[PDB]
Amino acid sequence: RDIDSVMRLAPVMPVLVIEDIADAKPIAEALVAGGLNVLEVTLRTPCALEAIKIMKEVPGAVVGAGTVLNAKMLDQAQEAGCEFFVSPGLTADLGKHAVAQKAALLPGVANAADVMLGLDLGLDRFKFFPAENIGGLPALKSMASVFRQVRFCPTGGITPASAPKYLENPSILCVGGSWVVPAGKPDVAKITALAKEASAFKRAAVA
Amino acid sequence: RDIDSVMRLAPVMPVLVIEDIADAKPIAEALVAGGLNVLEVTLRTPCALEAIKIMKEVPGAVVGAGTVLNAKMLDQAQEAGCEFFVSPGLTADLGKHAVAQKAALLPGVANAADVMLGLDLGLDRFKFFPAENIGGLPALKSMASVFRQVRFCPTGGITPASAPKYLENPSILCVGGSWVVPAGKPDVAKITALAKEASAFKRAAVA
Amino acid sequence: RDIDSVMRLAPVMPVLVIEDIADAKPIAEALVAGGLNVLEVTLRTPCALEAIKIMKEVPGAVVGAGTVLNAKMLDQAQEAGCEFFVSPGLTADLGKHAVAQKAALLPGVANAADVMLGLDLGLDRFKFFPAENIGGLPALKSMASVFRQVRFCPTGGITPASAPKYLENPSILCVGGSWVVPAGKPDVAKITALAKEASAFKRAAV
Image (cartoon, rainbow over all chains, first blue to last red; front, side, top):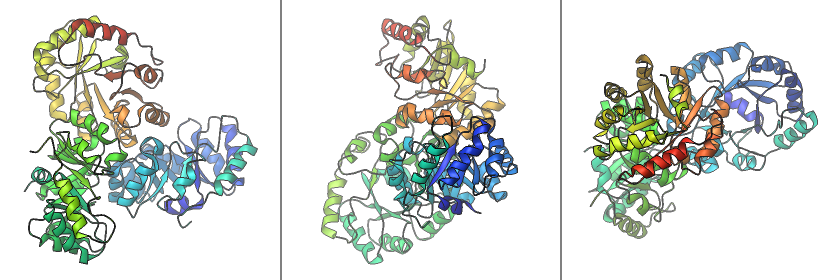
């Protein structure tokens, strides 16, 4: 499954920071019950690859790795069973490797030079990151109107209040956010409710 | 003619999106009558290279291509007769190719690394894009005071109201804007009047 | 001395634009008397390498070069006696060269791709520049929370009022600023007082 398809499965891609492996299964189950099957587990905590291997066992879960900073990490996340890969930015190295490896990479962009490098490598789906701190929807629209063939997932500072505005733009296939898994102790009921709310967001884009 | 000379010809560089080839000659005539000889035709529409070939026949018109994403597009724009090339960002590839080809490229920058990559390739004139979404004049002043040898053309969200503020800064040679060719149906009188207005903007950099 | 140590010496790294070589010694003396020993002399003026050579003779001065755009300029700044190097951004070339040369480079980053390139080269201390124009503390926090191993010095639009907010974040080791050497005629008393004031900023990191 290529990255464009992953982006269309759900309106919101939860960005998970797993601080305790005990939380992995319940978080994943709650998200999936709520209709958010596509899970980005960030490689920001030491227990992240275990957490991935655990969520991967949850039926319906499409588990990816975030915070993939280089080819090494991408290779590790792959071995662990990740179906796609998110990185906060793009380097030529990470890109060339993802392409070579047929890996569904969703790399971060912040400006035209980033997208252009992406395009040169044969990539056309990017994470706009960190969205709210680098110009927000206005900045993304400017990029979208220049790179017509490109589609985005904005992440960074997006909330339940701002997500539907981004999703009204057809250049945006989904948004990333952590508001869906709050605090630090998992409340399966709260998570499932926030996920239901979020999985019902309308998108302009043909999903 | 090198890119610095192009930038000094006029205070405003119209950013044209030509949707109907019938409009190319009249738009170009109107702009040139108005004192805006330097025309950026964006490669955002299917008829853009024809349009360039038409405007190129207009006496006094200095026609360039915008939205040049890669070396392929640059080569095509060149074959078509473009005198200069604008891109929304800069890659090492597009840059090395422009330099090699002696093409007057005016590439987009959004931050210091972009400028630094430009400088390494032997380029010192950049488009700051999309200006109003990446910090505006305050951001551009910061860059300008660091890269003293560099000069800019900001494009992106600039209006008749903001253009003279950018043009007061001597690091700015001109600005790009699309306000000069409004709507989608050409009014030669309106265009010429808006161009006269804009061609009389004072610039610190050019008397 | 590596770059992480330079960053910890003082809370504020003055960013100096020396417009007149006569001003170099007095500025450096005043800053050092004020407890800001770490001086970044930007290579933005024609007299900057002379200025560096002068400030380098000032006892207690740790002099670096700023606005190092490439390997050539780094090598020149080195020859002139600089102990560390700051650049507004990072290129693979400048980075590879700094690493190869064991030079304490503090390069500018503005987004994740910049940091990622840094990390690939073995660097983990960056200047976030120009801070106030590319998202400020909020943007920096977003970066810091993604790149947990990295530490920053924000520069660009920082003031005495905002500097302590940045320094409360433990990902930030120090800030750069020019407010400490005002105007364009040096007032040794004003400079020393502003430097004392700035040298007493608390930092979460140190």
